[PDB]
Image (tube, rainbow, N blue to C red; front, side, top):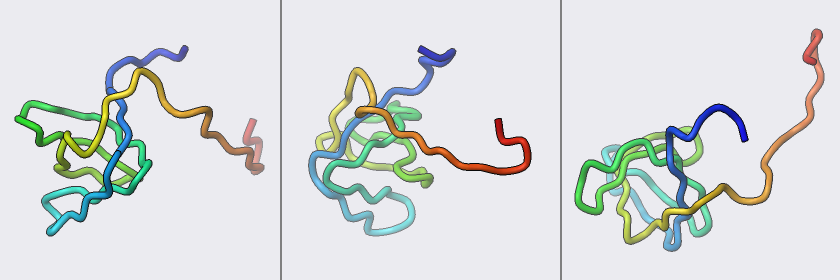
Length: 79
């Protein structure tokens, strides 16, 4: 599609409650951007704009994102 293929994606099967800021909170059916997974189960990525350490067993790697998330705004010569 678009020049990329750098970060992987995944869906949170079970909602995770990040005890502290160290970990990352996940919600049932949440797409997280896989940044780095150089750990056993402990994955690293951003959910909704916030990065952190979340479990793998909770999320599941996906081949492609879900449907198509986009919006249409207007401004000073937006496009």
